[PDB]
Amino acid sequence: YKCGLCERSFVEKSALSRHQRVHKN
Ligand SMILES: [Zn+2]
């Protein structure tokens, strides 16, 4: 799953969700 904001490919949506801490809109 590509973050869109930094498109790092997170294998699982859980990780993608967690990764938003990095930007959080
Ligand atoms: Zn990101």
Image (cartoon, rainbow, N blue to C red):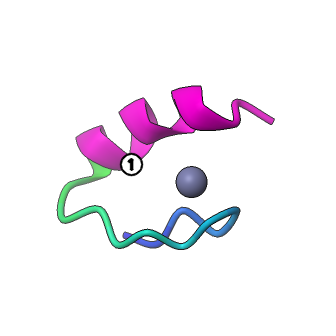
> Which quadrant is home to the N terminus?
bottom left
Residue located beneath label 1 in the image? 16
- By secondary structure, the bulk of the magenta-drawn segment is best described as helix
Residue 17, given in percent of the width and then of the height, sits at 43, 38
Q: State the residue at coordinates (34%, 72%).
A: 9
Q: Which residues are magenta?
A: 14-25
Q: Is residue 25 left or right of residue 5?
A: right
Amino acid, disc 1: Leu
- The picture quadrant where one finds residue 14 is top left
Q: Is residue 21 left or right of residue 9?
A: right
Q: Is residue 11 above or below residue 22?
A: below
Residue 23, given in percent of the width and then of the height, sits at 69, 36
Q: Is residue 1 magenta?
A: no
Whether the residue under disc 1 has CB within 8 Å of ligand 1: no
Q: State the residue at coordinates (55%, 26%).
A: 21
Q: Is residue 25 left or right of residue 21?
A: right
- The picture quadrant where one finds residue 10 is bottom left
